[PDB]
Amino acid sequence: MPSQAALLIGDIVHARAEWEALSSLVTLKEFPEGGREKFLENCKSGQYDDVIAIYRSNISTKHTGPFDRELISALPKSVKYICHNGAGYDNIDVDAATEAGIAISSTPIAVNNATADVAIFLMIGALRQAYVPITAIRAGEWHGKTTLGHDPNGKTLGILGMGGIGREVARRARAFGMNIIYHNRNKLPPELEDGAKYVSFDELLAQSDVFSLNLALNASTRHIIGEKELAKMKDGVVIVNTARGALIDEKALVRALESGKVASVGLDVYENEPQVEPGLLNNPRAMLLPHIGTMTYETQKEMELLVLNNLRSAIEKGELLTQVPEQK
Image (cartoon, rainbow, N blue to C red; front, side):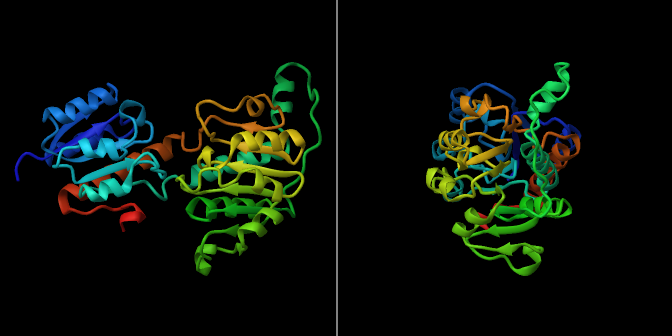
């Protein structure tokens, strides 16, 4: 009927022009900040009662809290679409949305290159324990206590969750001379394996020299790598995570670093970020970044544009471009 609106939660950094352009189709509304309590008050107040679609992002969670069952339950009945900026969306309760008649899109295949770039950066950092020489040169110590690292050449990269990101990690890692193995719940068809060898979960733990993971976070993949799994890995394994930190029992990871079971880690993500377990943060043999995977100009703008294109498709045609696989 008349009077459709779109609501922006949080900020749009790179694609403001594309957002403003949607005003030819709908009334543009914004919730740039304010907290969950105030967001819920706005919902109950009727002011969003014409909103058919919502743009939100992983970062914008700080302004509303997650789009969990409770928040979805408060959304006005008008809402038909939530277009999310991020390849991960573990802060949206997808089934609650389905029940409320809301379709969700995310941003898959825009994050792949940048995240993989950071995964390989982290892997080489971890294999060289590069925080030591990075710190030493700046301190005027030259090498300082730098120790010899290991070459990735001839070594096995194991990938738990071979998907778009994993394939781009594998492509890079092969150029470094690595052999690639992976485990998904189901073997991928040959073009999607793109050269990698399928193995069981236990075999992935046993055979990886560098172990990396790309899983969606959920109640069952939380701590999928815990004490038991670390104990199955090779002595001297290096672990890389650019996915979600809570996939690993970080306290168990710290104990495994401490015993020498794990030689090093290359992390971009953490179980309670922005907090990092102290024994992890304080370990100069670890290679650690503060979740910078997609923090580039080209990737961030591509991610925004994908969300806005989903929105425009939803409004004009009543369909999404990248609807989440749960609903599809």
